[PDB]
Length: 480
Ligand SMILES: Cc1cccc(C(=O)N[C@@H](C)C2CC2)n1
Ligand SMILES: Cc1cccc(C(=O)N[C@H](C)C2CC2)n1
Image (cartoon, rainbow, N blue to C red; front, side, top):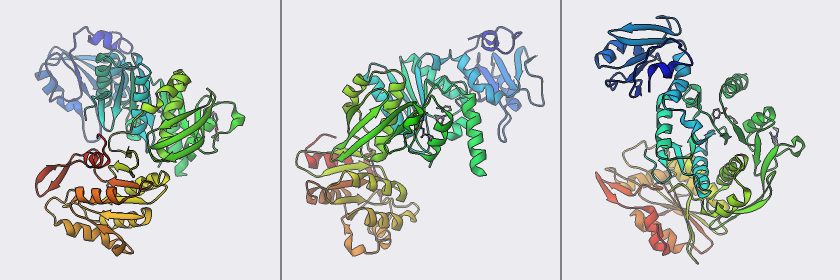
């Protein structure tokens, strides 16, 4: 890395100077670094140019606003300071060049929308890796090669993508937040494909702002959920986008690319999804639960088809796709009730989890759950009302009671019910889980909510070793 090569597209006359790393933080700007001095909300990095210089940086790139002209080269204490107008907008491009254009050196797929980003990215990364890629993810659960995901500016994004390319990644599925997009955090990334899952006067400016952003990015193949009203607006203006539906929203008159689920059977271990597409038809056995996960899987399928992965190979590998651990994670065993472990710990999340589970439930739906002690109490009766409404059997138990009296938490939950006497209460959590699993019938479904993959139960100030997954697995005679 050299300042002159780095800046060649923009600043013809920039001095040669070897560079080490790129940083926005004057506090970690080491000797040989490029410090980038950006102006944000209540922050002016140019204030810290003296400090960085004093810490021995090789060079500085700085916001030109009010201070200089675009491309102006100055020199302070023998250190080149190059000024650029609209530096926030350009930071992604600058960092891209610094880090050798990582998005041109793997297949990058970006997933945007309110929900489903995490699951859809995971599915993209898993399925592509099943077809021979070395895949990675960047998103809410962290960054890394699959299995090694470790728990944010335009520089950081490019740096992390370069790290992945360095570790041998050939495919990356990235969550792209609305906030990230607006703050130019992905501005110079070359997306192979861009996926839209869903959106949760005004409508004209919102739309306008997002269209403007779209027009400025390298989105690649566009893959859009046609079951969402906003998705259909995108599709109306993008004739080469791929429309995906599990209802009747594909308009066959447009002769565009499409994928639609024609029949879905939600069963005790997943969903059987029959589909047609402009690539051919097929049937997939998904091991994920609920309708929204059928949509997420279809989006991943359509994306991979769009990118040229063969339908036959995707079909042969689909049954290996797994849920994110502790997210609507299904446990079945021959002749036992189906048990779903989900992290749902809010009224809305609990409601969605119950509605998803219900689709797969021939019998009674059980819900085992509690609420955290020494935290806001407001959700407690709301979760009680939800469990009573959307399950057939509510089993109220403990969930990280901490220092709060466990039964007091349970009381708050029960207080939200129309008919609390119809709820079952069982303390200890392990005991409650066991109660549901051992009493439920073979065609029942038991949702164990609140913990997902979090393998502890906080009682007092002790983190006790405890896993919903392991509890369930042992009861069913399976392996967590
Ligand atoms: C770009 C494309 C490809 C295939 C089908 C379609 C499609 O059904 N569009 C619908 C949802 C129109 C109202 C927006 N659009
Ligand atoms: C991943 C990504 C990056 C940059 C822009 C975009 C974008 O405007 N996406 C739209 C929602 C398009 C329907 C797919 N998506």
